[PDB]
Length: 10
Length: 246
Ligand SMILES: CCc1cc(O)c2ccccc2n1
Ligand code: NA
Image (cartoon, rainbow over all chains, first blue to last red; front, side):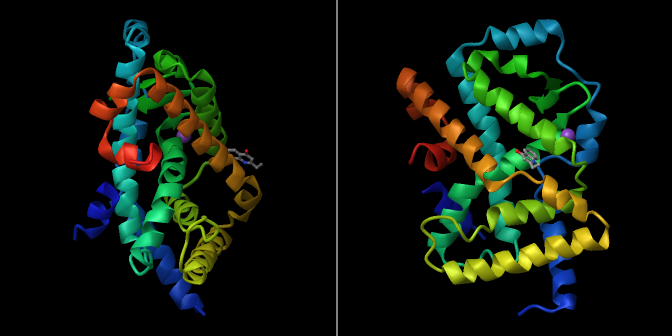
């Protein structure tokens, strides 16, 4: 969950 | 099939990505070296409960990892890999990059590390009940400090620690091998240009970084068995994603 969010947040 | 001009651009790009994603400027860490925890403060840390100390350490590790994620996102070619591969590389390598970055916050002159605003010895961490893991990390940081890395060398070396084509689970293994080969050229080109090729033989083997990460997960499992609700209710969600499996 967290890792996907950090990688998506541009 | 990268050229010399492209290799020099990659060196500058990695060094820039690293400078931008440092939690602490090296000059700030060096300027704090005389700011050492007193004996009363060390005693205070040693009297903390095992659970309070584990939560504080997991919070500090999580903050450091967040910067590594940002370093990866800025790293030329990383965002071009598929999301599965981005996650495989960060799950396997984030802690390894933090372990290498930690040598900047380690003062080899008195064997102290910058933690929660001041420098303290390994005795600061006695309440965790993972003496072997702590001493191995301090030994590792002491050995890296002996290499006298420049900020540009840490930048290039940490890019390679992260871009590792051997991680199990990579779907686009060839694409990662190509990025790893280009970063290896950038690193070795920089060392060659600055007459620092002697450090190549002095770098830790990949097995060393693997051993330290494995010891961390093992000590986490022991703590989790003793205080499961502390982990569930009070550990950072990113920390659990990387080291507990969610
Ligand atoms: C001489 C190679 C070597 C072997 C290690 O375990 C190391 C551990 C930490 C830093 C550098 C190291 N370098
Ligand atoms: Na150091």
